[PDB]
Length: 125
Image 1 (cartoon, rainbow, N blue to C red):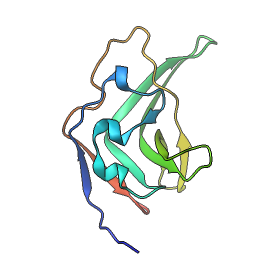
Image 2 (cartoon, rainbow, N blue to C red):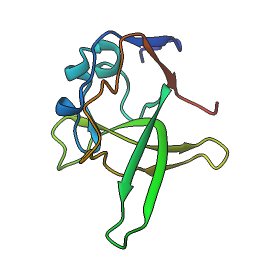
Image 3 (cartoon, rainbow, N blue to C red):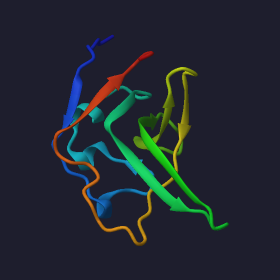
């Protein structure tokens, strides 16, 4: 039963919108070994909030901010695992998924700059 301490994970791999999945994240893509070897079910928080703006077909404009990343694995349909962003409710100890980021008129911009620090959360913050 291996034990590890909580330590910050820095990401040196930039992430571009063209390489950004609709709602998934890939640790291999960012070259983050620690995230890949991180325990399944691990909850990570990004110190850099991601704002996702989208337009509803009704004509309403909705804006949302996300900073929670969770790795799901151990699923029959999931061969290994995948990361998906959402909102982590520390007070309710519940997690909520998030919408996909889509830029139609917005320009391409680096969404994950080098120097971003992620923290491993394995309990209540």
